[PDB]
Length: 10
Image (cartoon, rainbow, N blue to C red; front, side, top):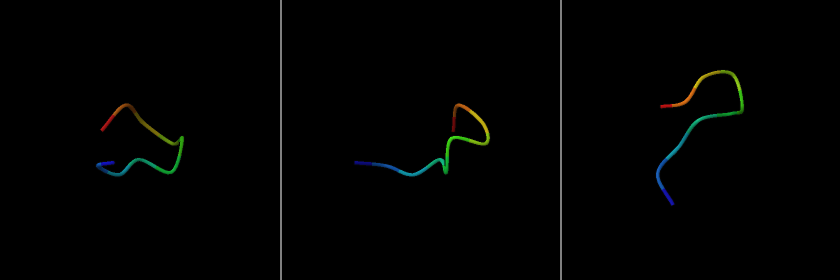
């Protein structure tokens, strides 16, 4: 796990 809402690689 990290982050990124699928909006941007992150």
